[PDB]
Image (cartoon, coloured by chain):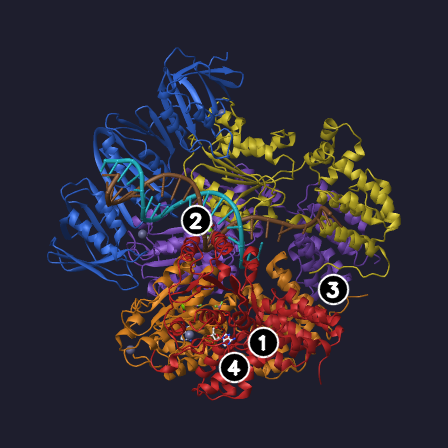
Chain colours: A purple, B orange, C red, D yellow, E blue, F cyan, G brown
Amino acid sequence: GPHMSYQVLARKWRPQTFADVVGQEHVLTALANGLSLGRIHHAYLFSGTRGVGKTSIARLLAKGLNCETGITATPCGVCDNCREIEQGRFVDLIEIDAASRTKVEDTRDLLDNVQYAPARGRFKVYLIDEVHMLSRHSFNALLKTLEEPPEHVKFLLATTDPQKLPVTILSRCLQFHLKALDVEQIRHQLEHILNEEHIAHEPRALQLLARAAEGSLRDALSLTDQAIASGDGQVSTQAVSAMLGTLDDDQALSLVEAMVEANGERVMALINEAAARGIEWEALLVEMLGLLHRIAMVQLSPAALGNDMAAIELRMRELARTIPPTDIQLYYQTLLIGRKELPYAPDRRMGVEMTLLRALAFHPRM
Amino acid sequence: GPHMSYQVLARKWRPQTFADVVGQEHVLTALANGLSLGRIHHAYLFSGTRGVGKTSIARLLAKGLNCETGITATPCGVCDNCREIEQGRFVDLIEIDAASRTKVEDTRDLLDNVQYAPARGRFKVYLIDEVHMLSRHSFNALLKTLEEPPEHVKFLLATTDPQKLPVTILSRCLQFHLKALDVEQIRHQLEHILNEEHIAHEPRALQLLARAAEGSLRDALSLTDQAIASGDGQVSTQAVSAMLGTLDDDQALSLVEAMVEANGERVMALINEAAARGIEWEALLVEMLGLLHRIAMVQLSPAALGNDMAAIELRMRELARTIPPTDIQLYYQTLLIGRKELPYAPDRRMGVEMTLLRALAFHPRMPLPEPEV
Amino acid sequence: GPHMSYQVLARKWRPQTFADVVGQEHVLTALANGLSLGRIHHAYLFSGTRGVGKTSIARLLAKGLNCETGITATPCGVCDNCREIEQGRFVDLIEIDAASRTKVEDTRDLLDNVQYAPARGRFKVYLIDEVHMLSRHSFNALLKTLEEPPEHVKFLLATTDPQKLPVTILSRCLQFHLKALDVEQIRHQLEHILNEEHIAHEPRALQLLARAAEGSLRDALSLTDQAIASGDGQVSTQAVSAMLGTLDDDQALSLVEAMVEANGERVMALINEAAARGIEWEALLVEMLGLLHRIAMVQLSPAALGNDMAAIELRMRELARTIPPTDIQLYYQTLLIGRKELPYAPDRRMGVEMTLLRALAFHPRM
Amino acid sequence: GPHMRWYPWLRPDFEKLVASYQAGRGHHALLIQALPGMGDDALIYALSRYLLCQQPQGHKSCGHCRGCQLMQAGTHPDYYTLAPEKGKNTLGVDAVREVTEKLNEHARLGGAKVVWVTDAALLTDAAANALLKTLEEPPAETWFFLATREPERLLATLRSRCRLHYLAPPPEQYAVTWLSREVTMSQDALLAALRLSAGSPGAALALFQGDNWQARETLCQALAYSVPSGDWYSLLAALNHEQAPARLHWLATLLMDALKRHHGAAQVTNVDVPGLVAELANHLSPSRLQAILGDVCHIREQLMSVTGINRELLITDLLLRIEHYLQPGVVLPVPHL
Amino acid sequence: GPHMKFTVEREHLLKPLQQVSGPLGGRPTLPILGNLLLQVADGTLSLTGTDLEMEMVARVALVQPHEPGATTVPARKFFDICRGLPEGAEIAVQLEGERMLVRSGRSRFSLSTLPAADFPNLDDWQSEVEFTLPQATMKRLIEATQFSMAHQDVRYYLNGMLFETEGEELRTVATDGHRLAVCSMPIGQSLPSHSVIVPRKGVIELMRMLDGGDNPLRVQIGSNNIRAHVGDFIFTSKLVDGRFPDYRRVLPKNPDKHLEAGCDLLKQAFARAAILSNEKFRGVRLYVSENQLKITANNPEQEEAEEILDVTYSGAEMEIGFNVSYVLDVLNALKCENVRMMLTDSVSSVQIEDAASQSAAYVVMPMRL
DNA sequence: GCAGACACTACGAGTACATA
DNA sequence: TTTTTTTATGTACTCGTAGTGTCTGC
Ligand SMILES: Nc1ncnc2c1ncn2[C@@H]1O[C@H](COP(=O)(O)OP(=O)(O)O)[C@@H](O)[C@H]1O
Ligand SMILES: Nc1ncnc2c1ncn2[C@@H]1O[C@H](COP(=O)(O)OP(=O)(O)O)[C@@H](O)[C@H]1O
Ligand SMILES: Nc1ncnc2c1ncn2[C@@H]1O[C@H](COP(=O)(O)OP(=O)(O)O)[C@@H](O)[C@H]1O
Ligand code: BEF
Ligand code: BEF
Ligand code: BEF
Ligand SMILES: [Mg+2]
Ligand SMILES: [Mg+2]
Ligand SMILES: [Zn+2]
Ligand SMILES: [Zn+2]
Ligand SMILES: [Zn+2]
Ligand SMILES: [Zn+2]
């Protein structure tokens, strides 16, 4: 049994070689140059937003550090050490789920055993995951070890929130900022993996997944698995559109034109109709934000408009022809605040109603 | 140079002589004069921000007090005690990681063995690092020992936030606050280190590293190591600028100039250029806010620009000569609100663009005209 | 060790007769009258501010009680036991650091040593330092011993925090509370030691040392030793001022002084000095808000100033009397808004500086 | 007592979800975005019944194997539940840590393992972080189930590692038909309850079953008394209870409908009570109505979020501030960016 | 029908009942958890106690004609109701509704019960491997490597023993990343190759269960749990899901430097040197020269200890520093006459084994200061 | 032995304090 | 003349109990 439970894409498609890593070119180049030149450090801190790949990058660094080929920038992936660390049975590599072993007793017990020799590999790599969840005493216990560790031990911290670490911990480590993946990178990676697994898909669906993933490969991959489960083995545009939440109709522009006209009757009728269609309120607010942004953008510079969708942008030119920029700016700010406070509402529909009523109250007479 | 296995820039270049410290003059002079005059207090606490030299200065004092020759402020590099303490595992110095010995059951064991005579040297130097981590009972145990210690025991207390110490502990010992380093000192130290290691460097990259170090030398030196890694073993302006994830002003100065001139087309063009470079959009707002804050600095007082911004100084002054303070207040507030609202924007580029649009549209001197009526 | 100057002023200048303790007349006279007139209690508990003389006065009581020339306030200092108490150790004076012996397994042995007759002196004297750290069971044992104390033993407990002691221990102990030394007494003493130590000095430096002492004479002596260190065996005004400026931590109060004074350069210099020390900026804003709230409360009523802010009482009183309430409310509003906007700033330093610049724009100088 | 009360609107989804597990390609972590009391617990329970069954058939458990018997009895070595401790509305990190440490050992019955959290929105930050990695890469044959009011309310890191299933509430006509079958009361009140429960039939049914309907009627009467006179303080007698957030939400919905009536919206959340909403619309100006609505919802959010807050002080201050807002010539709050 | 006729004698069950009780109901985790199951089968009464992790069953022989079935009762109540009866007692247990009535002469007591369907229990399962182990063999196997278990370490797979069966050999491997112990013994039975990771608690409970060479032990290992039958007692503990590391790649491959010495002399010397060793860093530095072993140690107080041993050494002069506790433990476990040590490099691990028998092996990983 | 005695070490509980 | 306190997690400390190593006259 080759770990059947790995059928989940997020567990099967994690890279095993530096070349397999998508994006993050700066940190990859820095790691490769450090390994090749011999400029090896003892405390790496990969910090970035969630689902970007710092755990996988750290595991690849550990693979490169503990390979029998030597201190190589590209792990072989077939040596005994590489196979063992893939299996997770490698003694010399210690993965600490710091969000669970956050107590200081465990940290002190671990640090009292740093002097001993590694079993097989050259280095005794410490993969401390979710460092920010350690207790303050646990942080302060790490200072002396991180400053001057023995030559056979290396700490590979990996946090999703670097600012919560004490400055004394950030000071001893090489901070690698894992840049959030762009839309194109996510789309290309999703296409590559789906074509590898022979799964039906449409480029538009992949574009929607990449845009709605909010700059994360793990989010995009989880959404892809959700779409696969929903659509019976195919990533179809209609299924992923109904799943993620899309506005194929022009009800967003109608809502904007009703609100900017201070037509509460039309605004509430459109809200009722959209709710009757099971609209996703957050995606709706995002669409209004985009429409208002394009309206202001074309108000500043003529043309340079929603030429992509000519139909609505004509009426958008009318809107930009009438509405003063200050009203557009305040409408956008109020919609954004409503999106921010949408979770803090008894109901999403009620939150959208709050946002639109606040927008109406600015110019209720006109 | 030798650079045996390149044993980290931070660890390799630790100070070894009182003339090698990068300029904590207010504590260096006091320690040298106390050692010269024989006024060797039995307890003193080093405090200050991260990576300034508290532990290094403590090791230097142990060097000076354990030297085979007379007690001097200039320890020799040939002395057996000095060599041992440089390599560690010294007989007299007792490295005590207080964070690993917070429990009073260990401080009592420490106190039980204080009276035994040192094997070598003169003063059994107790170097307690991260003193603020000790438990309350540990501090109270340390109290009477610090008040009247044995004549051959010196206490070397170091921490980062002395205010967490009990006040009587602060009373029993001297206090040395190590100020954060200035930018020029950091730059000179980085130049020295890179020259001694024979690595190509440029003035702008080193100035950027010093600015990003935020006054702590260990941060500067780790950042220099990471920049060496980022380049092909060479420190350059492009490499450091890419690594720090920021733009070298200028571009942001053009951004703010197009903002204050109500040149929305130029604002959009520069945003497109930044997108082509692919810089962090929050970095754009942060740098623009920083430049507006520096212009406010210049507005308050003319002597508010350092050499770091000298490359644009003549330009920057002209900004403070034309923008009324209330207009810069409005600009800073609008950009700050935009940064507040950026994470909830439909897209980060969308949020930055809308922030710039709001900043230029609310411009009092050149507002965006109402379209028709 | 080498050369007599190694003796720390906090140790060498330990008072040896009741005429040497300074500023504690309300306890010295009571002890002298009790010893002379025969009035005596089972136990005497000392308390007060750090470095005021509790342990020194307790040692003086131990000297006085155990001199063969009669129980008297003033010991001769010539005979065997008077010197043995100070130089070397005296058998019948039992000095116990309660912090080192908190567990009941040591106080049990101590009270097993109370039934034995004293060797040299008439009164078996116990001096227990830091009695507020004994364990609860140790406190029970000590109370059991104090319930029926033999006539040949008298206890002496010295502590800094009297509130932690059991009420049943306070009930049987005649507590002597020592007030913090006045600035004039500290200055006169420092001048006395400096003149008698052949150390040059200047009166303004002595006044600065006394003010910075915070009332504890040990703090004054330590700062004196550091001032001698900072320089060449000379207490110069410039060296003392520089050292205090290096060690000063009242950035917030001097900063609000400069802000209300509308001195922008002073505010910027103070921000620079706070940055040099690595002062937490959010903590600085919180402390400033607290100071503004307290000064407003002072304006409402002079009773708002308690003993907690005796060090900065005069400055806050004078800055309350000279400043109208409206400026206080405007500054509080500006600083609160600035703290609200501080996290969303390019960095904490520029954010707090920008808040201060916003505050300075109100009612500026020519 | 309350148990696996299966609901018809779960039928299309359940048959789907089990399919994702029938092929063996299902995600180990399934976060259910379902409104409270709508049926997420029953669906998760049935899914776990299918998963832990040694000899299952089709889309239901056999009910004969020892796993089914142990599951029915409420004790099972391979069925862990993470629920708030009795008397405390939070899920400590200690329970999550104990469960995660137990997951290391094999399943006792030789089958799979199930870890079901009753409500992921009640996770403490420490507990959710302790569950992060366990969610990411669980051992062989390990299944996680999470339920939430709002997925975005969860931690931004935990929600990333989970396939998210959304349970769509039934259309309003279907829901009103179902509740009319379940409860024999007026159509207006039933529709008002469904709209109050955000369209979730289960929450409206629970509202009618409990005393919450009587409390809502009393609050409506108190509002009717207080609107013309401004005696909003009396509302405290109806507002202060262990279920204060629900009554604050009812007041917020009433203000919603008053603003709608001023704007003339065709449909309203409170259709059963037209007199009170008309009185609120005519007596109170929309400008002050918006401020009162915002303050009421802010107080509701504060009361829900921070645990240990005192209901008496918050509700009393809200009522006093509302009364102050009623008086003319008083500045009104503005939403903060 | 409520038959449940239990007819047993008290003294023949008090020791089994105390055995199966063990960690009896004291945990309020589950009401059913704090209970013991009585079952009748094969002419014997099975007493089952389980806390969802460890299961213990006593098979006590019956006396009189019985009535098959099963029901669970409060464990503490049953333990206390038969521990005070004078000497022997004719325990007659009967079912009445949801009640057990226990009678013996003029002594009638009641215990409210629960049906056996609710009690979690393991039925028959296909064993992956089966062992017929002499008690001495397993006792030596566990004893010589029990000290090498990881005590609550981050690596969860190290929290126990690896029972690896290969051919007609059974091996136990225990390590924590600093020490390692391997003990292999023959069985004379063709057994399929398999690997088992039994947790710390399971092996400790198993170790304090077997005694007396008169009752051979029967071990049944499946894919999810391990069961041990000692006489009439049955123990069951779940397995660890992890994968134990390849120990044959942990032992040094080319131990060029050979040392042989007396076990007693080495043990005495190491204890003597450890007298003055560091309190929490009990590590000695050992120099090997031609037929000479110099062991040295010190403390922060600098109370150095030094001793010289006359050994049979083959190799070059060498320095290596290792902790004393692991080596004292290995030497104590190796109740032998000659200890053979294998050394490769001043940075490599040290092997320790019996010089007169190739049945055990130990690895000590040195200290790199 | 040996088991008691004694030594010693670990765990729990009850209490106190810190932090956000 | 009887009335008032928020949580969740962690870190020490001090004490009795509780279980076990070991070893000395028993
Ligand atoms: N740079 C990358 N290259 C390839 N896959 C990636 C990358 N980053 C993330 N992934 C995908 O995301 C999944 C989780 O990645 P992970 O490294 O755990 O992110 P994190 O930094 O948030 O812990 C991986 O299994 C892999 O499929
Ligand atoms: N004043 C200084 N002079 C020279 N190097 C310094 C100085 N301060 C810090 N460093 C560098 O930082 C490294 C560690 O400094 P350290 O003294 O540990 O800072 P900390 O005060 O945080 O413990 C040193 O090895 C040295 O290279
Ligand atoms: N009233 C005083 N008179 C003279 N010296 C004092 C006085 N108070 C404190 N000191 C100085 O401080 C040193 C320590 O004083 P001590 O009485 O131990 O303070 P504490 O109250 O904290 O125990 C003494 O040696 C003495 O030099
Ligand atoms: F989610 Be990752 F470990 F930052
Ligand atoms: F990093 Be230092 F010792 F504060
Ligand atoms: F400094 Be005192 F003896 F508390
Ligand atoms: Mg990770
Ligand atoms: Mg240090
Ligand atoms: Zn390899
Ligand atoms: Zn020297
Ligand atoms: Zn005398
Ligand atoms: Zn079944």
- Identify the mark at residue A325; answer none if there is no mark: 3
The three-letter amino acid code for the residue at tag 3 is Pro
Query: Could you tell whether B365 is left or right of B320 in the image?
Result: right
In the image, what residue occupies the spot 73% across and 58% down? D335
Q: Under tag 3, what secondary structure?
A: helix
Labels 1 & 4 near each other (Cβ < 8 A):
no
Labels 2 & 1 near each other (Cβ < 8 A):
no
Both labels 2 and 1 in a single chain? no
Quarter residue D204 falls in: top right
For the residues marked 2 and 4, what is the alpha-carbon distance in whole angstroms?
73 Å
The three-letter amino acid code for the residue at tag 1 is Ile
Quadrant (top left, top right, bottom left, bottom right) of the C terminus of chain A: bottom right
For the residues marked 1 and 4, what is the alpha-carbon distance in whole angstroms?
35 Å
Q: Position of residue B143 (x, y in %)?
A: 45, 66
- Disc 3 or disc 1, which is closer to the eye? 1
Q: Under tag 2, what secondary structure?
A: loop
Q: Nearer the viewer, residue E71 or E259?
A: E71
- Identify the mark at residue A14; answer none if there is no mark: 2
| Residue ID for mark 1 | C271
Q: Under tag 4, what secondary structure?
A: helix
Quarter residue D208 falls in: top right
The three-letter amino acid code for the residue at tag 4 is Gln
Q: Is mark 2 within 8 Å of ligand 1?
A: yes
Q: Position of residue C25 (x, y in %)?
A: 57, 75
| Residue ID for mark 4 | C189
- Disc 2 or disc 4, which is closer to the eye? 4
Labels 2 & 3 near each other (Cβ < 8 A):
no
- Disc 2 or disc 3, which is closer to the eye? 2
